Amino acid sequence: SDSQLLLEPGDRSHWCVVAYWEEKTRVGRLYCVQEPSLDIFYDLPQGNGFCLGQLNSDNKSQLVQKVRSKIGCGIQLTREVDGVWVYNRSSYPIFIKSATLDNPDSRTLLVHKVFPGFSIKAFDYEKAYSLQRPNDHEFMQQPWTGFTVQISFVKGWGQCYTRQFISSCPCWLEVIFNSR
Amino acid sequence: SDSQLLLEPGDRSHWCVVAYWEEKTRVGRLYCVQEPSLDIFYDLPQGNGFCLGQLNSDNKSQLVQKVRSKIGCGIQLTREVDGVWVYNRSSYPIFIKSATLDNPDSRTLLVHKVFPGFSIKAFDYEKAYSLQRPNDHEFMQQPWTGFTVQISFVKGWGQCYTRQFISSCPCWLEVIFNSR
Ligand SMILES: [Cl-]
Ligand SMILES: [Cl-]
Ligand SMILES: [Cl-]
Ligand SMILES: [Cl-]
Ligand SMILES: [Cl-]
Image 1 (cartoon, protein in one colour):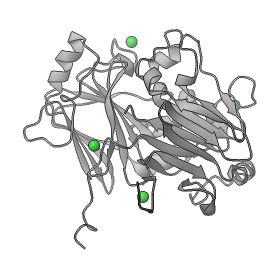
Image 2 (image 1 turned 90 degrees about the horizontal axis):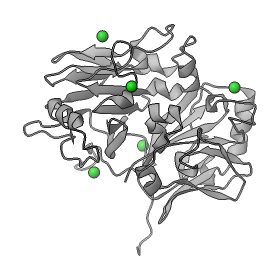
Image 3 (image 1 turned 45 degrees about the vertical axis):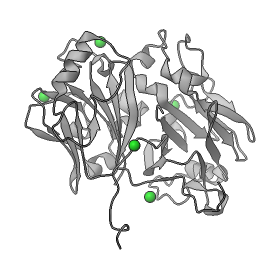
Image 4 (image 1 turned 90 degrees about the vertical axis):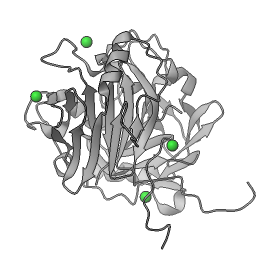
């Protein structure tokens, strides 16, 4: 046409970027978010946004298939006046690690459980802007942890769970937040 | 606010995301790249791209100020049919860590020096697609390392340098790559 052929340049206005993982395998392209709210869900009639059921995956594991069938309506991420909220719209708990959810003086970040229908503030811009975790050596060596949130469907990880690391979880998300 | 519309919250077409760092401080908003090539520079005549001199950094270190100016014309990042290439357009070496630059059987990833005027394939889609590093425990625990490239201007880090960690470098980039 006239405007249908041109490719626009990039921008600084996408407020987060989402990566979907199955265990150690990244599934599908990254989803870069512009509008203030996004559903992340399994099948097309179940939300407006990032559809995970459409992603072609090489991981055919039975456990991954079972968790995928439990994602259902998934989660919603929404920018609000006081930060970014994650709402659990699905019928199973989700588990979240975010640097802005924890006491800045702790030695390690915790994984937080969010029951179906409950919400949690995934990201706080003011706290992230000034965040130092001086007692967390891994954090100081990997400061991008300050703006990357990890979310697992159905299965928890870390202390008091079978899986020590998030990359053992069947279905999980990496959410990278812009500073904004 | 008054008319119905067909919302798409985001897109999959930005092929990498660039974060600029000064030591342990993230500086400026993330840049989501859609154009085939991106110039990243401190000062480039009639330059159009990701200008690091315009950002208003909180890092007031004199070393950071000196290195920032040395970036000069910076680097060029180009997405091509055969992968993503980095061209060093500055007067100083740059230093790059990328999982697709290394022997997959090694224990830890190396930092690679790129002279002024030289190029390197910073990211290879097919090598990354299902890259496994079975002797690298950190990589298996943090598989997103396989899609993220770190680039430092002027100053090296790692094995052969006083700086052990990337977050000790005065001026560096985190580049998060999308899949093909
Ligand atoms: Cl912009
Ligand atoms: Cl484990
Ligand atoms: Cl798209
Ligand atoms: Cl080298
Ligand atoms: Cl160091």
